[PDB]
Image (cartoon, coloured by chain):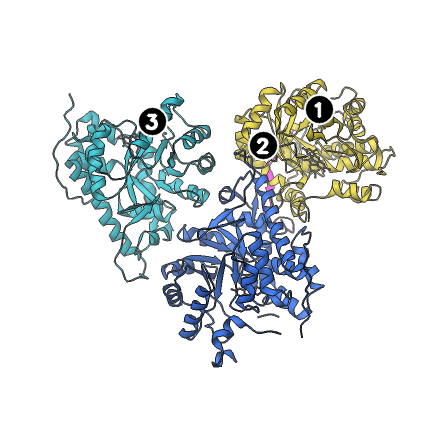
Chain colours: A blue, B cyan, C yellow
Amino acid sequence: EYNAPSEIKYIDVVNTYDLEEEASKVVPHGGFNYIAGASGDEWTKRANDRAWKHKLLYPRLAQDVEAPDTSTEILGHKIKAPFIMAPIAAHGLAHTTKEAGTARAVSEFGTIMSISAYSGATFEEISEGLNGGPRWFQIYMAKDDQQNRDILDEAKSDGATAIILTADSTNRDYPFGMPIVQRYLRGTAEGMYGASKQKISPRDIEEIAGHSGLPVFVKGIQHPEDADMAIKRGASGIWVSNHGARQLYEAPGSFDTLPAIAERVNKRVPIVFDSGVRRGEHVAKALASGADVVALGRPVLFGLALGGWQGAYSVLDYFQKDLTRVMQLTGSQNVEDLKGLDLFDNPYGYEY
Amino acid sequence: EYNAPSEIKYIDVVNTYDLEEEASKVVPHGGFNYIAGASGDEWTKRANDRAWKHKLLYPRLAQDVEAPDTSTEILGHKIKAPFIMAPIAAHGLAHTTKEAGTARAVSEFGTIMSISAYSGATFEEISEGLNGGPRWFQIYMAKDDQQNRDILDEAKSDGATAIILTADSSKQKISPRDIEEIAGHSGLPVFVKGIQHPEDADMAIKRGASGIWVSNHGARQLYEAPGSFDTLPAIAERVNKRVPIVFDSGVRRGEHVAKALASGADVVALGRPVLFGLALGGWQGAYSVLDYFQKDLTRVMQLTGSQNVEDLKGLDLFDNPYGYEY
Amino acid sequence: EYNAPSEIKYIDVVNTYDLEEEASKVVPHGGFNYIAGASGDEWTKRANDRAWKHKLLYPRLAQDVEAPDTSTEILGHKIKAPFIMAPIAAHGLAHTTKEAGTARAVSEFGTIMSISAYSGATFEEISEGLNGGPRWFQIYMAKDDQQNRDILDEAKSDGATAIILTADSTNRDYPFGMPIVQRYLRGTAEGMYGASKQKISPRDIEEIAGHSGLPVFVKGIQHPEDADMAIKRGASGIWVSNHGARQLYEAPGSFDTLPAIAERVNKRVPIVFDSGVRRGEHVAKALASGADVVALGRPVLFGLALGGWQGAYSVLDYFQKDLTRVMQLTGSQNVEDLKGLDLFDNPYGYEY
Ligand SMILES: Cc1cc2nc3c(=O)[nH]c(=O)nc-3n(C[C@H](O)[C@H](O)[C@H](O)COP(=O)(O)O)c2cc1C
Ligand SMILES: Cc1cc2nc3c(=O)[nH]c(=O)nc-3n(C[C@H](O)[C@H](O)[C@H](O)COP(=O)(O)O)c2cc1C
Ligand SMILES: Cc1cc2nc3c(=O)[nH]c(=O)nc-3n(C[C@H](O)[C@H](O)[C@H](O)COP(=O)(O)O)c2cc1C
């Protein structure tokens, strides 16, 4: 049917870019393209990557004697480093252990797992990987209110401590099901993508926030006015993202949108940043630019492909270790120091 | 002998600027100049005032049905509106009830009292006026380490819930080292007051400050310096949520409170206008000024489409490159 | 063990870029990569190079009748041209004559030799090459104060006339020892990289400046506030560098950071600039931008690989000759004239 990698092993991650080409060797071409690809000719995916060169880190003298500490807290969860796992569908395309494998890596590492509504694994399978670890549940806005009630109940029953409401549903130049949604779509026509609204409104955000009983992050924000509207509608977090360039084409690199959003949010709610994080330097730059944590996506999936949970763990370990080095060089003892970094504005962009 | 005003009465505050001239009629000349005056020819005091015209508010549509609510919280304490009382010395120059009067107005209103290092009332006198209300103690850095340890113990025993370390006086200027010494021994969150440069904010936080208090002390210290409000955004962007920000120096209107919040302050501190209210009516006069700011802020919230203090933190400001003369 | 080149000969240096590929042919692959490589994917090494195109030289009419003179003075040492040798570890990776070979080229040319704490040559070997020439000693900040006392004593005993305190210790996508540090680390656990603080503080600078009995340059400065802090802590010089892009990744090209630092230093102490100097035009641009001298690194090492001391000398000679031509074209009679040059701001960057 679909011959996903099944090997479990640690990997020596020197950088995350090479994981893409390495994964291409073990992942079936179709599944690999699904994971790696983006809208149009990928210009906005390239923009997500090149945006990091727009603001450059300065090395700075230390002001504290202690060894660097990457730990932080979000929504009262203490986590080992300022990154969490982004919600990503169909991990089975990368590895036979699928979302259970990712959840194991995330829980063992000591951060938060985001569960896609479109998970290929059952929650029971994921739960076994999580082994008590914190988890957030990502949902789409259903056209049918009953389906929103259903998924919100599922999330709470599954011990979710936040909801991630993704603003965009579903663009470029599927071997298994989705048990988590099928659980409540069975016997309805919707269970036989189109069940969700293509785009959410402030009214949608207000409905989910009122009925979730959990803090709601609105994911896919790129414009500061949307951030303000979302918070006024009852969002408890803003998740700055263009979903790894998988949706709107010929849009800005995600990092370029972050400061304007952070300035408008002005501490009202936590900010999660994603779309293009590949290096420890990127984590630091996002924090310096107003994010509280970043979310990791494709690199963790490529690690999963290459080594199951241990491969995914290796990627998380890479980010933590690289971040520590960046902290040393920038004179930062802790995650809060990173939030205070001055960045060099590079008007020349990528080619310098 | 000094004949300070002694009457206690509410006053109809239409604007705070007029309180200065009105207070000049009742406060002895020497004391009044001490309160109203600033360094040099007062150009930086004027700059504190004119800076508010550099960033202008937009009227905007509402997105919530509820009436405005000015309440906020700082360091876990719920307060009626996003402003506190600044530490000011020698309130007896303004009114016979001195700091007890101001403390009464502040506690009756429902916000935080800052107690100056150079208060003319005893703690017992101030405590009576506070009636259990929250208070923060402002200190200068003593050259003697034991005097610092003693003042910090005294503050904590007197029920202080924060320490305000004023950067400019005692040592005439503080260093990161000084901040570290105070933060390490206080048992309370320490605000560093008098910050105008973002690198100082970063150094202070790294040295152990639990808050940054953006201030030029109402233009009473360095002359030919920027208006305090112009320094706020750069500091806020560098602090980047690490610790709460108190802003002061020039707040005269509800619009100023809104603009400070939109620019990264958590609360502002009020100074001269409250003292002028005290001169004019004792605690009830000072209360009248706090009430004015609360009511004026409520109007500004309505007009900007803001239901609560958080909405204020999200406002967009119009950049006015023309400055005061437009 | 390690088959370093040993031939001694002059080389016809047409440009320094070609010396890299030429050296790659004679230097063992491992040692060559150590010398040539930089952090991440080398984007910041490329930035060091491309930064030179951000400020362009104007040809200008002459105002003096005399022939150009490249001589200058720093810390009262008169030197033949406004460049010195940067401190670089393990010259034996390039050539069997190692640091003695470099020191000979530098001393014969008539400039200052910087001695890395991580030299592969003994001081006695280096001294023979130096033959009385001026030398500065580069140190790292030891965690153990005794080790700092030791190296400061070594430097003075070796006739050093300045200390170079490198701010960063030890990042990318060793056949011999270090006799200079082993001399005082022997019998301690440290002698059996981790002995130094990862990053220095102003307090560290103050300690070294108070106990050195010599002017102390703080090396690795890229931010003006660090320059001010370093000077207030007792530094007698600022050495603007990102260590040839070998430390912090996704940082600015070193030359782009120089004017802001020079403006803050405001003549208080001399400035040494390095990281990417490849041409006489670069020396001129650095001087026009506030440096007193530049330091040369990789090109001198590649020359050493290709021809021992005579090869290294050829590179120094190339820079002096090329600088002279630049002086003629810019209407400059002397090094001071270079400090007064107007540069053309190029907002387009490298691709123009
Ligand atoms: C294979 C793939 C599937 C994804 N599925 C979802 C999804 O189910 N829900 C969602 O909110 N985001 C989804 N995302 C977007 C991610 O949450 C995240 O925003 C993105 O991976 C970040 O970009 P990066 O991985 O390039 O750094 C997916 C991304 C990819 C790579
Ligand atoms: C009369 C006078 C006395 C002051 N005394 C102190 C003091 O004891 N300690 C201190 O930190 N600030 C002191 N300040 C500064 C205030 O805390 C505050 O920063 C200032 O009043 C704000 O400016 P504004 O009142 O013009 O808005 C004083 C200010 C004035 C007006
Ligand atoms: C092979 C290599 C080893 C180095 N070792 C040291 C070192 O021991 N101490 C130090 O302060 N800098 C060291 N550096 C950095 C240099 O002092 C200098 O900053 C750098 O070579 C300048 O960049 P460029 O050679 O590309 O022009 C080293 C650089 C390289 C190329």
Residue A29 position within the rendered picture, expressed as x and y whole percent measured from the top left: 68, 69
Q: Badge 2: how crowded within 10 Å, few (<14), some, or many (20+)?
A: many
Residue B209 position within the rendered picture, expressed as x and y whole percent measured from the top left: 42, 36
The magenta segment is C341-352
Disc 2: which residue: C200
Disc 1: which residue: C184
Residue A314 position within the rendered picture, expressed as x and y whole percent measured from the top left: 64, 53
Image-quarter location of ligand 2 = top left
The answer, for residue C107, to whether it is visible in the render is yes
Q: Badge 3: how crowded within 10 Å, few (<14), some, or many (20+)?
A: some
Are dots 2 and 1 on a single chain?
yes
Q: Between disc 2 and disc 1, whose residue precedes?
A: 1
Left or right: residue C12 compared with residue A24: right
Mark 2 and mark 1: Cα distance apart in space: 21 Å
Mark 2 and mark 3: Cα distance apart in space: 34 Å
Q: Badge 1: how crowded within 10 Å, few (<14), some, or many (20+)?
A: some
